[PDB]
Image: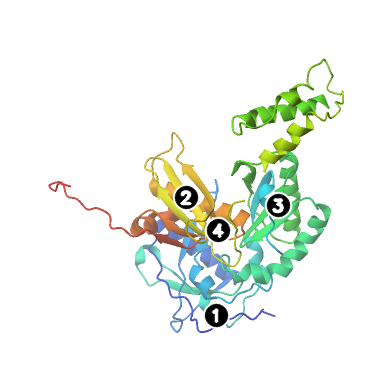
Amino acid sequence: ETVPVKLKPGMDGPKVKQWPLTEEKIKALVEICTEMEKEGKISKIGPENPYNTPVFAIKKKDSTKWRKLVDFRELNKRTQDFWEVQIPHPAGLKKKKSVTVLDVGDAYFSVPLDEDFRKYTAFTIPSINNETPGIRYQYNVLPQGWKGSPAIFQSSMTKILEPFRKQNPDIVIYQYMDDLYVGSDLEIGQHRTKIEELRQHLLRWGLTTPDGYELHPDKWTVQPIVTVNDIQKLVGKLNWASQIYPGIKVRQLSKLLRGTKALTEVIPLTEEAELELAENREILKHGVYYDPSKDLIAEIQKQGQGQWTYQIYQEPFKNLKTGKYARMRGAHTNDVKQLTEAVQKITTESIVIWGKTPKFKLPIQKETWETWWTEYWQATWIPEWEFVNTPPLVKLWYQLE
């Protein structure tokens, strides 16, 4: 029985023009869709259907095989709120040594979609070289990219993950849309095989996965701190921290390090050193509070060569996070391609940290972005974005600024 779903009250279905596509991407979309139809994942529809949603084709990682990407941003805004289902967002996830991202989207296609709602998923596939009108389809199954899919597939996913979660209590698995984020502190080799065990478990359920994507949230921000061998570790950490806090205490701890004492030797804790340790922990340890009910906003500025700066906030001037991205040496300069990668990363961070995608303000012209962005986009999701409003300067040769 299809889980009944409704649009938000007083809201109609999405109508969004389908953007023009390259012959190559079209030829891929046609072939992809022809097969989705044979499998009954989608069905042709008649002229009686007003609604439309935009579609494109991307390629993930090194894969030369095309993936279809539908833009549900409108539909998702207009869809009912599933929050009843949502399991508070894990804070520990961002702490983990390694976090891998799996695309579970294939799972959704085994679940039928409510017959009443299907009309709203309508999309148009342009023909080759626009020789004939485009063909319009809809979704008979939970589509990838629609916020309803994960909410409705929740119970089923929980069942699939249960055994592995029981078997690995120290591994955190968190889902956002079509992606499964698996964190852990395990040695990278151990972690990797844990992912592979997972992938083989999901495969037992018929759920197929593409090779994972490795993240190291450890390296996103600069971080707080934590036998004779151990006392050397501390002293080394304080000396390092000394270049930061001039008040860090050293000599008292150094006084205990004089000797031939072996690694095994256990040094006693003197009342002289403990003062330096308690005061050090004291210099170790505010910020701005994050409100789950509000929205995350991300502003991006271009710093002029390879450089881009960003801030993430809710109320202006109060920033939850600020950072910078820079173009690699030896990389061609393409501002859209670079900006596209920055947006995807900032989003990945927001997803991992607050479990939410920020609304973007992009330092670039609307036209440029909307033309190019799909070329460089590797993500299964798209955020909301807004372009700074200024007109670009148009100057002919014979004109003087």
Residue 310 tag number? 2
Percent coordinates x, y for residue 399 in the rendering = 14, 48
Q: Is residue 22 visible?
A: no
Q: Left or right: 315 with respect to 287?
A: left
Q: CA distance from mark 4 to mark 3?
A: 24 Å
Tell me what residue is drawn at x 74 percent, y 39 percent. 187
- The residue that label 4 is drawn on is 380
- Choose between 11 and 180: the one closer to the eye: 11
- The residue that label 3 is drawn on is 92
Residue 276 tag number? none
Lower position in the chain sequence, tag 1 or tag 3: 1
Residue 8 tag number? 1
* Mark in front: 4 vs 2: 2
Lower position in the chain sequence, tag 4 or tag 1: 1
**Which residue is situated farthest in the top direction here?**
260
- Where disc 1 sits, the SS reads loop
Mark 2 is surrounded, within 10 Å at the Cα level, by few (under 14), some (14 to 19) or many (20 or more) other residues, namely: many
Mark 3 is surrounded, within 10 Å at the Cα level, by few (under 14), some (14 to 19) or many (20 or more) other residues, namely: few
Q: Is residue 127 visible?
A: yes
Asked if residue 44 is positioned above or below residue 87 in the image, the reply reads below
Looking at the rendered structure, the kind of residue marked 1 is Lys
* Mark in front: 1 vs 3: 3
* Mark in front: 4 vs 1: 1
Q: CA distance from mark 4 to mark 2?
A: 22 Å
